[PDB]
Image (cartoon, coloured by chain):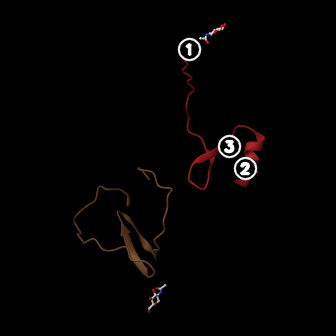
Chain colours: A brown, B red
Amino acid sequence: INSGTTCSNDLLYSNTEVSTGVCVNYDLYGITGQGIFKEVSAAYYNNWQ
Amino acid sequence: DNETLEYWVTPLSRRQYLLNFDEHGVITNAVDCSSSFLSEIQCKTQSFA
Ligand SMILES: *[C@@H]1O[C@H](CO)[C@@H](O)[C@H](O)[C@H]1NC(C)=O
Ligand SMILES: *[C@@H]1O[C@H](CO)[C@@H](O)[C@H](O)[C@H]1NC(C)=O
């Protein structure tokens, strides 16, 4: 629950930009919460992570 | 040409480990928490030293 790609389109919204620097709410493909984003140049993700 | 077929098999069970992840996110060390006394100290301190 609250992670994955089998999503329910009962409540439909539009995709927004991943804005950095500001305190926002987020709904990142299931993951919900509040916080601040910051774009980084990461190299530790595989094709399945 | 001096070749050999080898197929080593061991059973599995559900148990707790202590895993070590490095900078790049690779598992480099592991310790079975119920194998010895040093493993007990390593899993109670959550440290590999
Ligand atoms: C604080 O406010 C300024 C402008 O009012 C904004 O640019 C900045 O992102 C805000 N900082 C946080 C952490 O929300
Ligand atoms: C294969 O192993 C034997 C061991 O007695 C050795 O004498 C022989 O030279 C080996 N053959 C090759 C091609 O390495």
Of the image marks 2 and 3, the number of the one nearer the N terminus: 3
Judge the density around disc 3: few (<14), some (14-19), many (≥20) Cα neighbours within 10 Å. some
The relative height of residue B2 versus residue B9 in the rendered view (above or below) is: above
| Residue drawn 55% across the image and 24% down it | B9
Asked if residue A24 lies left or right of residue B12, the reply is left
Confirm whether circles 2 and 3 share one chain: yes
Confirm whether circles 1 and 3 share one chain: yes
The amino acid beneath tag 3 is Cys
The relative height of residue B29 versus residue A38 in the rendered view (above or below) is: above
> Which residue position is annotated with label 2?
B48
Marks 1 and 2 sit apart, C-alpha to C-alpha, by 38 Å
Residue A26 position, x and y percent, is: 38, 72
Name the residue nearer the viewer: B13 or A45: A45
Name the residue nearer the viewer: A47 or A33: A47
Marks 2 and 3 sit apart, C-alpha to C-alpha, by 12 Å
The amino acid beneath tag 2 is Phe
> Which residue position is annotated with label 1?
B3
The amino acid beneath tag 1 is Glu
Residue B33's disc is 3
The relative height of residue A40 versus residue A47 in the rendered view (above or below) is: below
Of the image marks 1 and 2, the number of the one nearer the N terminus: 1
* Front label number (1 vs 2): 1
